[PDB]
Image (cartoon, coloured by chain):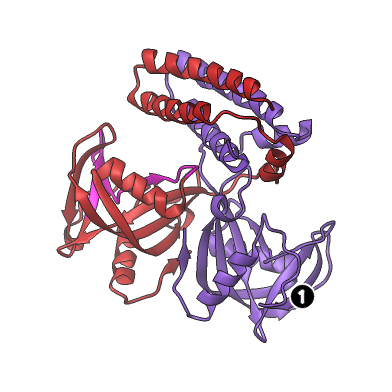
Chain colours: A red, B purple
């Protein structure tokens, strides 16, 4: 593909993205258009010919099948209490995290989720568990739920469009849990792994 | 622009656009994402030598939720040699495994694939690594590649419709690898984790 054809596609996509940035009324759509606009701008700066044979060989294999969905969670313990967050408009609590996003590794995914939800930079210590939601919180979609032990670094919690509150809870004083995201049984297993009283948990 | 960066940009923009289609509640935002997906499809056609079937395979929506996909692999060592399999119609070798199927847990998935491919029942001993395919073997889809250390139990290898051959190889006498499934660098890393020279590998 020639540079001029690449520029054509990029400019057409930028037009649509800019329209989204002007007209959308939804903050989560706005975030997506901001992400797209940033990527497209970088791409335009880098516009060049592309080796279409090389592109095809990097893309292969092209066939893909549905798998369980990636979910990432952070296990953060301070003063023997666990960090839980409560979503906007929700009355239940869960470990920070959410869907794994394409374009980020497993550890980068949890760090991205921690920063966006909690307002803190963080470090990943270890993977504590890989849970199957079919075992612990059966739902219409199946997830592979990675739970990483993490430490918070610099930052500050700020209520935002995703998260209404962030608090630390003793395991014998847990609040109402969002079961589809984390259960008391999972928290108890995680505490055992965290304290080195059993090995990494795998479903 | 580098080929690898083009593929990562495309992969990411497909994921964002698909997330917009699933989550937006406004018909004009829906149309914007649809128009973006049409442009991504046109750009991919022009940027790559993929045939029409292959292009459709890349663009076929795999899921309503765009996340990295599951791939599972088995690390089986006997007499200090590593089990590799060669698929029917293929000249190269990989660790047993494949994509994670919905309806099975991560360990159940690897045990199922070990039995189907190698003819053996097995035990999962530990998780050795979770690799990001975007790092080690970039391809159209991003996978979280779980590599489980496993021990074979009862059974027998028989050539079947999926697998042409199964052999054990010394760490320093590896055959030609199916790199989109496993690389020499990954095998070397895995050997170090397996031998306890370093901890679990996580991207």
Along the horizontal axis of the image, is B194 left or right of B173?
Answer: left
**Quick check: B171 above or below B16?**
below
Q: Is residue B127 left or right of residue A159?
A: right
Task: Find the magenta span and give its range.
Answer: A83-103
Q: Position of residue B80 (x, y in %)?
A: 65, 84
Determine whether A62 is above or below A27 in the image.
below
Q: Residue beneath label 1, please? A: B167
Q: Callout 1: residue from which chain?
A: B
Q: In the rendering, at what x and y percent does residue B50 appear? A: 75, 35
* Residue placed most toward the observer, B170 or A189: B170
User: Is label 1 in a helix, a strand or a loop?
Assistant: strand
Residue A99, given in percent of the width and then of the height, sits at 42, 44
Q: Count up the numbered dots.
A: 1
Confirm whether the magenta stretch covers residue A112: no
Give the residue displayed 19% in from the left and 36% down from the top: A159
Where is the N terminus of chain B found, in terms of image quarters? top right
């Amino acid at each position: 593909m020639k540079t001029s054809d690449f520029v054509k596609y990029l400019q057409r996509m930028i037009a649509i993205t800019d329209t989204g940035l002007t007209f959308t009324k939804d903050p989560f759509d706005r975030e997506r258009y901001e992400d797209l606009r940033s990527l497209l701008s970088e791409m335009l700066n880098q516009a060049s010919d592309l080796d279409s044979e090389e592109v095809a060989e990097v893309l292969k294999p092209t066939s893909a099948y549905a798998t369980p969905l990636m979910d990432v969670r952070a296990w953060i313990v301070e003063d023997e209490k666990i960090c839980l967050v409560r979503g906007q408009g929700e009355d239940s609590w869960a470990l920070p995290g959410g869907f794994g996003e394409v374009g980020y590794s497993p550890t980068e995914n949890i760090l991205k989720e921690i920063e966006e939800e909690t307002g803190f930079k963080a470090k990943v210590e270890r993977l504590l568990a890989v849970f199957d939601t079919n075992r612990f919180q059966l739902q219409s979609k199946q997830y592979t739920k990675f739970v990483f032990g993490c430490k918070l670094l610099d930052g500050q919690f700020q209520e935002n469009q995703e998260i209404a509150d962030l608090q630390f809870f003793a395991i014998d004083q847990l609040p109402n849990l969002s079961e589809k995201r984390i259960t008391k049984e999972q928290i108890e297993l995680l505490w055992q792994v965290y304290q080195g009283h059993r090995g990494q948990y795998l479903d």
